[PDB]
Length: 98
Length: 364
Ligand SMILES: [Zn+2]
Image 1 (cartoon, rainbow over the protein chains, first blue to last red):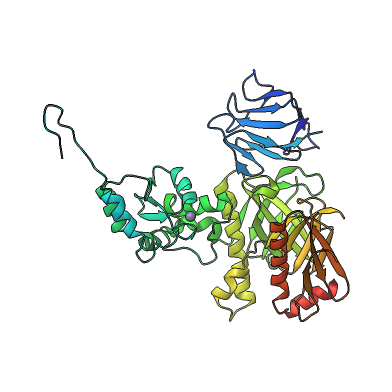
Image 2: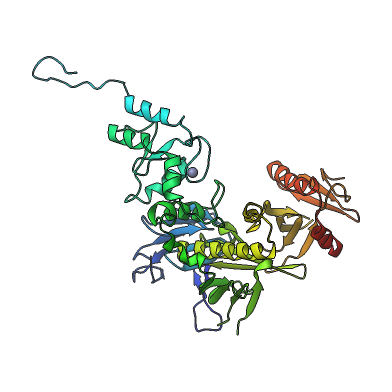
């Protein structure tokens, strides 16, 4: 269970993969499990939860730039394998579920 | 009026006279459709712009409070001055003011278009006032544009920043790698917004048809305005190209050729699940939606020319395409989709083939 950075150039010394936890905090703060910095990202920006029963749910924080498969999202939404997430300006990721 | 005594209560009543007046304004010429997307029977209003708009468009108008304040025609209370503004304005008035100088090649969205198109149309008109002051139209009117776009790597699927140049002088779109990497004749280009497929709100599909093979390119810009400017620059370039390549042809005849949206797209089984695109007469299928090239293609000619679509099998639902040579069998998940697909194929069948379409058929 991981997030693929779709903008990582394989030919560069760039991080491609972020593994998710059961409860994953995403944002710019040191406290976040996946720490992303850049335009349009909040200290606390998003939350991904993996349910006991294998279900993946994304919960945006208020007032955040958040799209799933190209459309904006402002309440909890279930993710599937291969779903594309945009956070902020250009934090563009793809979801791999096992 | 009031009540008798120290309390002296004011009573308003059920009059709703102002709402009533605004409602009648909906009956006036030009107000029958949403000012912005054309949807019938608008039930919202911007009282600072003096337009009548649909629910969806009103939500976009709400994102631009400095320009537009919106009220429901029925569900909101109105002030007299607000009703008066609407009475002295309306959708026709707004066309002359805000749609005064819209270039003929400029894409006007419909209700089914993606959010980006609808939002940028509203923003261009009212916020930027792009069609009041023609200077503002330079990004897509100069016949030349360059800039970086995030493009999907052909096989590897990563979107990386690459330079693009659209030049009407040379009649081409090109891009450069990390001399151009590719040069694509405008004759052979199409562009279509595909935010769901690409998984990005600003996702634009550019296709390039060379030697009966279509290359899919997928790009986006971080800025919604910039990507819509690219789109309309592409349309400008096609338009200018078509005016010179086909003089004697009216602008009206040329404008629907500028860029084409797909009739229908989706997974069907063929039994293997594949992503299908109906681009006119040309049914393509892919392993993944974002593949650069189709796995295969099926041409759909006319009834005349020996083509028919059938329901059922000779997934639950079935469609059969009978070609002069072979039969093609497809499985649809649902009956809505089956209906839509069949409708798409029927549109090809019901229409007489052109000389170029015979050339395409000959290949397949
Ligand atoms: Zn509308």
